[PDB]
Length: 203
Ligand SMILES: CCCCC/C=C\C/C=C\C/C=C\C/C=C\CCCC(=O)O[C@H](COC(=O)CCCCCCCCCCCCCCC)COP(=O)(O)OCC[N+](C)(C)C
Image (tube, rainbow, N blue to C red; front, side, top):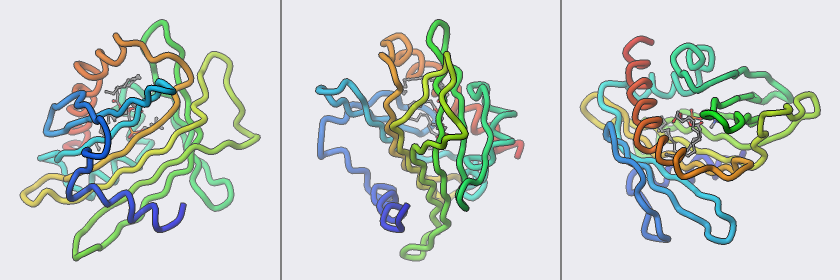
């Protein structure tokens, strides 16, 4: 990915930009808000996530976000996850546990972190994008996510936390049901965010 992309992801870290389209708020918990935008022609959603995470340093947060070995230990929604280098770049394989009776979703993607200093500010940017390799074909019974792009930008809130901004889009390869969106919004994601906070405490 080009440097532009790294500097572009930081754009809304300071002032969230949700006035361009119909961004509807989905969940507000642990000082984190998650907004979604629907594309009515396709049925697909985009997501943006902003807030702060008090009681977890920004540098350590960037570290737990890229530490897959640790991720597997504390995150109960990771079925399988491992990294490899293909052409000098880190390719990640990630299988997400979906609730019964839906199939699990798996991701093959490029991932790259850059620690910046813009306007004297410590910021950490993580970019992720969908790729394919012949050596890692599709698994029967696991939906391969073939369109997927994510950004994350971490910063200090000022006292003793991390200010964050994340953009997320994928095509999940099937009709994500309303009960699953409801489950994720009201239980899944809140429980995940607190598990993740706990994960900073025990690094
Ligand atoms: C900002 C820094 C603080 C940490 C991140 C903050 C907040 C993350 C929470 C939501 C982010 C917003 C929207 C994304 C919506 C769905 C995500 C899909 C499953 C997933 O991967 O989500 C984990 C997050 O884990 C979970 O929430 C576990 C609970 C869900 C697991 C199963 C869900 C089934 C499908 C749900 C569909 C409806 C979703 C509606 C959204 C409320 C992402 O983590 P990651 O950034 O490390 O990337 C992992 C690498 N990967 C993506 C390639 C697999």
